[PDB]
Image: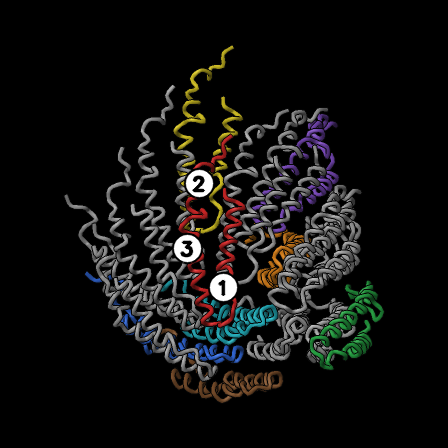
Chain colours: B orange, E purple, H red, I yellow, N cyan, P green, R blue, S brown
C-alpha cells in the first residue's frame, strides 16, 4: 500500500541540493579551512571546499529521494 | 495454516528498497560525514555513504520479505 | 514546501563576502605571516594573504547561499 | 539583518594601520635583523624592515575592515 | 473547540526571543568558551557564540508559538 | 505577561562587562599564556589576551541582557 | 545589585603587578632561557625576559581589576 | 589582603643572586663551552660565560622578588 | 516566627572559614596536585591550591550564614 | 560551639611538614625525574624536586591547620 | 599523636642513598648514554652520569626522611 | 629493614665490568666507527673505542652496586 | 549453500578496475605529488602515480572478486 | 552425539576462502592503503595487501571448518 | 549494476586538463621558481614549469576518468 | 557542468602578465643582482633580470589561464 | 589457626619461577620487541627481554610464597 | 602439583627457534631494511638482520621453555 | 605438535629469492640511483644495486624459511 512515512518530503526542500542547510555546511567549511591554514600554513584544507560540494552533489544525486 | 502476522507488508512499502525511510538514512549519513570531515579533516566518513547503500541493498536483497 | 531552516540568512550578512568575520580572518592572517617571517626569514607566508582572499571569494562565489 | 559580530571594531583601533601592535612588530623586526647581522654579517635581514611595513600596508589596505 | 493548554503563553514572554533565559544561555556560553580557550588554546569555542544565537533565532523563528 | 525569570539581573552585575568574574578570566589567561611561553618559547599564547577581551566585549555587546 | 563574586580581590593582591606569583614567573623564565641558551647557543630566549614583563604590565594594565 | 603565595621566599634564598643553583649554571656553562671549543676550534662559546652572568644579574635585578 | 532550623549553627563552627574540614580540603588538594605533577610533569595542578582557597573565601564570604 | 571534626589533627602529624608521607612524595619524585631523564635526556624533570618542596612548604605554610 | 604512616621506613633502606634501586638507576644511565653516543657521536650523554648522582645525592640529602 | 629489591644482583653479573653485554657494546662500537671511517675518511670515530671503555670503567667504578 | 553476501557485486562495478572511484584516486594522487614537488623540489612524488596504478592493477588482479 | 550447532556451515560458503566477504576485505584494503599513501608518501601500506591475503589463507587453512 | 559514485564527473570539468585548478598550479609554480631563482641564482627551478605540465598531461592522459 | 573553481580569475588580474606582483619580482631581482655584484664582482647576476622576464613571459604565455 | 586459603599452592607450580606461564611472557616479549624494532629501528625494545626476567626473578624472589 | 598451563607447548613448536613465525620476522626485517636503504642511503638498517637473529637466539636460549 | 602458522609458505614463493617482489626492489633501486646521480653527479648510488642483491641473497640464505 502506501508507506506511511511517505508524503511530506519537504524533507527534500529542507535538505535539498538547494537548501539553507546545505549552503550552511560549505560556508563554515570555507571558514575553518581558511582558519586552519593560518595556524598550519600547510596546503591541506582547501579540498572538501570543492570536494564536499561534489561529494554533496553525488550523494544528493545518489539518493535524491 | 495462515501465519497471522502475514498479509499487510505495506511494511515492505514502508521499509522497502524504495521507501522514504531508506532515503532518509543515507541523507543524514551524507550530512554527518560531511559534517564530521570539517571537524576531523580525515578521510574517513565517506564510505557507508556508498557502503551502507549497498549494505542496505544486500540485506534488503537478503531478506526482501 | 518551505524548508524550515530557510528565511533568516542574516547568516549571509553574518558571514557574507562583506562581513566583519571575513575581514577578521585575513587580518590575523596578515599578522601571523608577518610574524612568522621574522622568525623564519623565508618567503613563505605571504600567499593566502592574497590567496585565501580569492579562496574566500571563490567559495563565497561558489556557495553564496 | 545585522551580522552579530559587527559593531565593535575597536578591533580596527586595536590592530589598525595606526596601532600599538603594528608599531610593536617592525620594532622587534628592526632589532632581530640588526641582531642577526652581527652574527651573520650577511646582507639579508634588512628587508621586511621596509617590506613588512608595505606588506602590512597592503594587507591593511587589502582588508581594512 | 478551544485547546485547553491555550491561553497563557507568557510562556512566550518567558522563553521569547527577548527573554531573560535566552540571554542567560549565550552569556554562560560566552564564558565557557572563553574559559575553554584558556585550557585548549585551540580555535574552537567561538561559534555557537554566534551560531547558537542564530540557531536560537531560527528555531524561535521556526516555532515562535 | 511578565516572564518570571525577569527582574533580578544582578546577573548582569554578576557577569557584566564590569564584573569581578570577567576580570578574573583574562587574569589567569594572562598567566597561563605567560606560563606556557616559558615552556613553549613559541609566539602563540598572546592573543585572546587581547582577543578574548574584545571577544568578551562583542558577546557582551551582542547579548548585554 | 551587588555582583556576588565582588569584594575580596585579595585576588589582586594575590596576582597583582606586585605579587609573589608574578615575580615567580619571570624568575624561572630567566632561568630556562639561560638554561636553553647553553643547549642552543642561539640568541633566542632573552625576550619575554623583558617582553613578558611588559606583556605582564600591559595585561595587568589592561585588566587591573 | 595577603596574597597567599607570599611569605616563604626562601625561594629567593633558593634562587637568589647568591645561590647554589645560580653558581651551578655558569659552572657547567664554563665547561661545555670549553668542551665545545675543543670540537669546534671556533671562537664562539665564551660569551654567556660572561654574558649569562650579567644576563642573570639583570633579570635578577629586574625581578629580585 | 522563628525558623526552626535556626539556632545551632555550630554548623558554622563546623564548616567555618576557620574549621578543621576546610583545612582538610586544601591539604589533600596540595597533596594530589603535587602527586599528579609527578605523573604529569605538566604545570596544571597548582591553582585551586590557591584558587579554591579564595574560592572557599568568597563563597564563605558569600554565604557566611 | 565546638566544631565536631575538631580535635584529633594527628592529621597534622600524619601529613605535617615533618611527616612520613611528605618525605615519601619527593622521594619518588626524585626517582621518576632521574628515571625520565635517562629516557628523555632533556633538562626538564629537576624542578618540583626543589619546587614541589617549597610548593609543599608554602601550602603547608598556607594552611598548616 | 603518632602519624600512622610512620614507623617502617625500610622505605629508606629500600630507596636509601645506599640502596639497590639507586645503584640500578645510574647503571642503565651509564649504559644508554654509552649506547646513545654510538648513534649520536655527540658529546652529550655523559652528564647525569655524574650529575644525576649528585642530583640523587642532593635530593636524598634534601629529603633523607 | 631489608630493601626488597636487594638480593639478586646477578644484575651485576649480568651487567658487570666483566659481562657479555659490556663486551657487546664496544664490539659494535669498534665496527661502526671503522664503518663510518670508510664513509667519512675523517679521524673522528676512534675515541669511545677507548673512551667509552674507560667511560664504562668509571661509571662501573662509580656505581659498581 | 549460498553465501548470503553473494549476489550484488555491483560492488565490483562500484570499485572495479574501471570505476569512478579508482579514477578518482590517481587523480588527486597526480595533484598532490605535483603539489608537493612545488614545495619540495625533490624528485619523489612521481611514483605511485604510475606505481599505485599497477599496484591497483595487481590487487585488483589479485582479488578481482 | 550430534553437536547441535553442526550442519549448516553455509557459514563456510558465507566466509569461505572463496566468498564475497573475503574479497570485500582486501578490496577496501587495497583502497585505503592507496589512499593512505597519497597522504603519507611513505612506503608502508602495501603489505597486508599481499600479507592479509596469505594471512587470510593460513587462518582459513588453519581452521577451514 | 551502476556504481553509485558514477555520474557527476563535473569532477572532470573541475579538475580536467582544461580546468581552472590546473592552470592555477603551474601559475604559482612559475612564480615560486622565478622567486626562488632570485634567492638561489642557481639553474634549478625551471623544470616542472614545463615538466609538471607534461607530468600533468600524462597522468591526466593516464587516468582521464 | 561548471567547474566550481571557475569564474573569478581576477586571479589573472592578480598575477597577470600585467600585475603588481609580477613587476615586484623583477624589481627585487634587479636589486639583489646589483647587490650581489658588489660583493662578487663576477658577471653572473644579470640574466634572469632579462631571462626571468621572458621566462615569466613564456609560462604566462604557456598557461595564461 | 589455619588460614583457609592455605594449602594448594600449585599456584606456585602454576606461576613458579619454573612455570609455563612465566616462560610464555618473555617469549612474546622477545617477539614484540623484535617486531617493534623492525618498525622503529631504534634501540629500545631489548631490555625487559633481560630486565623483566630478572625483574621476574626478584619479585619471584621477593614473594616466592 | 601440576601447573595447569603445563603440557601443550606446541607453543614451543609454534614459536620455537625453528618455527615459521621466527623465520617470518627476519624475512620482513630483511625487506624493510633493504627498503629503507633505498630511501635513506645510509648504512643503518643492516644489523638486527644479523643482530635480531642472535638476539632471537639468545632469548630463545634464555627462555627456551 | 604442529605450529599452526606452519604450512602455507607460498609466503616463500611470495617473497622467495625468485619472486616478483624481490625483482621489484632492485628495479626501482636501479632507477632511483640512476635518478639520483643525475642530480648529484657523485659516485654514490651504485652499490646496493649490487650490494642489496647479495644483501638480499645472504638474508634470504640466512632465513630461507
Residue nearer the viewer, B30 or P26 = P26
**What residue lies at 48% left-to-right and 85% top-to-bottom?**
S52
Give the x, y percent position of residue S45: 54, 85
Res P28 quadrant in image: bottom right
Depicted H50 relative to depicted E46: above or below: below
Residues beneath discs 2 and 3 located on the same chain: yes
Q: Is residue S11 visible?
A: no
Q: Earlier in the sequence, mark 2 or mark 1?
A: 2
Left/right placement of residue I51 relative to residue P63 reads left
Q: Which chain does tag 1 point to?
A: H
Q: Position of residue N17 (x, y in %)?
A: 49, 74
Nearer-the-camera pick, B50 or I15: I15
On-image quarter of the C terminus of chain E: top right
Read off the chain for label 3.
Answer: H
Q: Is residue S29 above or below residue N55?
A: below
Circles 3 and 1: CB atoms closer than 8 Å: no
Q: Please tell me the numbered disc located at residue H9.
A: 2
Name the residue tied to disc 1: H46
Amino acid at each position: 500500500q502506501d508507506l506511511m512515512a511517505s508524503g511530506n518530503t519537504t524533507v527534500k526542500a529542507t535538505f535539498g541540493k538547494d537548501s539553507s542547510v546545505v549552503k550552511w555546511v560549505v560556508l563554515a567549511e570555507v571558514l575553518v579551512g581558511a582558519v586552519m591554514y593560518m595556524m598550519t600554513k600547510n596546503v591541506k584544507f582547501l579540498a572538501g571546499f570543492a570536494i564536499i560540494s561534489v561529494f554533496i552533489a553525488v550523494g544528493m544525486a545518489v539518493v535524491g529521494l
